[PDB]
Length: 219
Length: 208
Image (tube, rainbow over all chains, first blue to last red; front, side, top):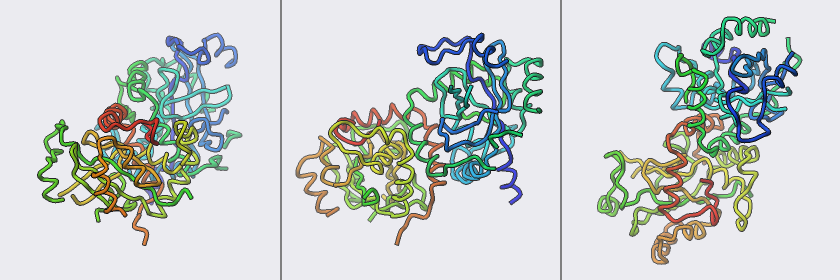
C-alpha cells in the first residue's frame, strides 16, 4: 500500500514544445521565437488534446536559446491510479529502466506511452505518443529539478527562470480528469498507427541530448 | 450488436518462411502430424477471449479460424472503440463501420501459436511472418479474405467452425498496449505479412 502510494505521487514532465532550430514542412506548426516571447512576456495538461482527459497543469514555460521549454505536473488521482494498474501489466515496464535509476512503474508507463509533447492554440499542452513538431520529447520524473537536468541545452540561468516559476495553486486543479481506462485504451490503438513513431522519437531524444543523460525515456 | 461474436482467421505459420530465429521453425510434417485450443490476448492465461474452432494445413501453411466470444472482453473493447480516433475514421469505402471489429483489427493484428499446439494468441504482431489476423462477423467472409485458400480448403474449415473465461481488465489491455508501441519494425512486419497473404485494407478491416 505504501509502494502503491508512492506510485501515485505527483509526476513532473518537461521538454521542448518547439525547437527554434527545427523548420517544419507544415506552416501551421511554425512557432518563431519572437512570437513565443511576445505572448510569453496555468495552462491545463491533457492526454492527446482531449478536454475530458485533463491530468494536471503546466507549471512553467521558458523561451530559451534553442526553443520553448515547459514543465508540467501530472496530479490527477484517477489518471495516476489507472496508469498504476496498467503499468503492472506491462512487460516493458517489468524490464525496468537503465541500471542506476530506481524502478518507477508509473513514470515508466508514462514515458513509454506519452513520449511526446504538443502545444496547441497559448491554450493547452498535450501529452501524446509523439509530437508533430520535432524535438518535443517528453521527460518524466518525480522531481522538477531532476527533469530539467536531463536537458543539456538548459543553462543554470535557464533553470533559475523555470524554477522561479514552478516554485511559485492552479485553477485547473478537485480531480480534473473526466475520462477512464477505456478512453486511454481506445486512444492507445491510435498511437500504434502513427508512422515512423520510434524514428521520430529517437531523432527527438538525440536532438535534445537526453541520450547523453540517464532518464526513464523508453525510446 | 457490437458485442456479438467476432471471428478471426489467418495463418499461424507459412511453410516457405524461414524465421530469423531457430525456435520459430514449424515445418509441414510436424504440423500435419499433430493435426479446442483457447484463444487469448498476447499469451496471458488470464486473458482468454474465446477459442480456435478450426485448423487446416494448406499449401502455404497452417490456417486457423477462431471465435472471440467473451462478454467481458467484448464489452471492454466496445467501450474503448468509441474512444479511438482510428476507429472513428471507419474502414474503406465498401465495408460498413464496425467499431469492435476495427479496434481488434488495429490492436491485435497478429496471430501467435505457442506450444511446450496449446494456444493461439491475438497479439499486436506475430513473431512468425505472414500471421496477419483478419477479423469479421461472418467466418465465411473471413476465409474469403485469403486468396491462397481454395474452395476445398474452405470446405474443410467450414465443417470445423460450423462461463466467461476472460479474467483480465481494461488495465491489463492498456499495459499490453505500451509494450506493442516498442515492438521494432511492427508496421513494416504487418505490411509484409499483409503482402504475403494477399489481404488488402481495401477489402477488409485490416488497419496496417
